[PDB]
Amino acid sequence: EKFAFQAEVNRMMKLIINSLYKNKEIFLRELISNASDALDKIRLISLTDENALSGNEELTVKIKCDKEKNLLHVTDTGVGMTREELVKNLGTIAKSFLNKMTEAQEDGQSTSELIGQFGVGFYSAFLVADKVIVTSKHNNDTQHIWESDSNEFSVIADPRGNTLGRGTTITLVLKEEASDYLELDTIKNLVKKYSQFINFPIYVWSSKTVWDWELMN
Ligand SMILES: CN(C)c1ncnc2nc[nH]c12
């Protein structure tokens, strides 16, 4: 159940952290960017599979804050990940760079748009999270759970059964010095800055006292 990151992924994580060390808020931009790519992925698949959305009819990205439990949730109803995809897509490299990141970093150029361009921004979550939990269900597999603290990662079958229907949930156990992102006004502002150009609706579980979703894009 326990795996070690591929060495190249260990290096990529450090390069992404050092590049976005001064602008940690970018992690939420990438999580949104990733959630869109997953939704964009299942929508293309729906053009060829009439039952690709049977597990879940909505195509949304929903965000929840839990100040009491110190958690931040980013859920998308996209294509999702199988057990094998949780291990390979997150633990190794398998798409399409390291010299370019080093060259831009060594020659002192900016790389924020470079990480979001290749879609490796998932690891920027470790800028604000002590642990990253990924719950995902793919139409061709059962719902699994992926956990990591940047030192290793594990995958287990979700004992709660099929809860998501289809999609992924990125759960971040925010650090002690990242509780600023537990407040609502800061999250809603950050979400709106990065979710305008996403072709899918973005909801945030806010309060007013009753609670409900709030559209941001
Ligand atoms: C992390 N990664 C590459 C992902 N793969 C598939 N669906 C996702 N939804 C959010 N991130 C996702």
Image (cartoon, rainbow, N blue to C red):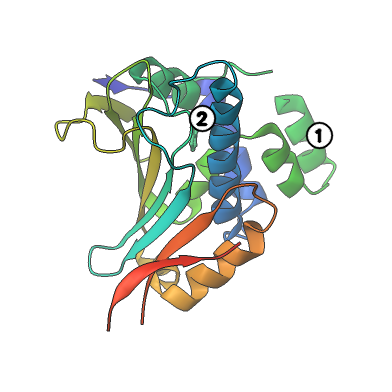
Quarter placement of the C terminus = bottom right
Of the two numbered discs 2 and 1 on the same chain, state the one appearing first in sequence: 2
Relative to residue 171, is residue 61 drawn left or right? Answer: right
Residue type indicated by callout 2: Asn
Residue type indicated by callout 1: Glu
Please give the name of the residue rendered at 44% of the width and 42% of the height, measured from the top-left corner: 58
Mark 1 CB within 8 Å of ligand 1? no
Please give the name of the residue rendered at 55% of the width and 53% of the height, measured from the top-left corner: 201
Q: Nearer the viewer, residue 103 or 92?
A: 92
Q: Is residue 145 above or below residue 68?
A: above
Please give the name of the residue rendered at 85% of the width and 42% of the height, measured from the top-left corner: 107
Residue 176 percent location from the top left of the image = 35, 66
Q: Are marks 2 and 1 in contact (CB under 8 Å)?
A: no
Q: CA distance from mark 2 to mark 1?
A: 18 Å
Residue at numbered disc 2: 10
Residue at numbered disc 1: 103
Residue 192 percent location from the top left of the image = 60, 65
Quarter of the image for residue 48 reads top right
